[PDB]
Amino acid sequence: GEFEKLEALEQLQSHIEGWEGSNLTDICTQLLLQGTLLKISAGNIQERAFFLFDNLLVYCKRKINGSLYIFRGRINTEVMEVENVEDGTADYHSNGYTVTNGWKIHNTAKNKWFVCMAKTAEEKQKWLDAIIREREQRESLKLGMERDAYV
Image 1 (cartoon, rainbow, N blue to C red):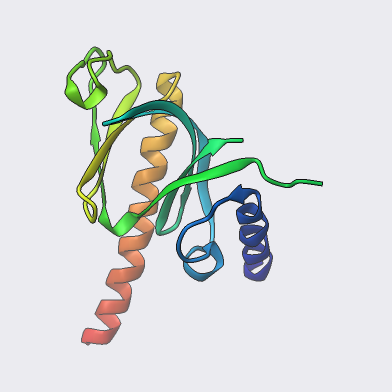
Image 2 (image 1 turned 135 degrees about the vertical axis):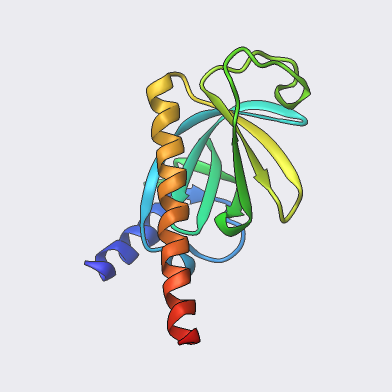
């Protein structure tokens, strides 16, 4: 059940070297989606492993040693905005490269942007659907709590 998923979070995290910040078992309960995406940011174009948990987005560099990943960054999804990018778009946000099957993520706490690109339209849709689901579940929990605190 829930305890088993907490142990699974601890194990998952054990495959990530150089973790920064609070532990997954303190702030997450589930993994909605993981996968490799091309990440384009001000000074880098590289593939990253992305993990979307309830409340958190993590991205890593792909690396008996259990390390598979090297920590690169995390975003509290409460301060994450996402914006679609239409195919064929090329501008400074993608460092002039043509984006297809891509979208933008805004870390509003650090005011940092980056572009994510999947390899296929179906993969992009899986990511957008998961981002929507993570936000909807989180908002539902929050509004339920506030409603019970209010009435």
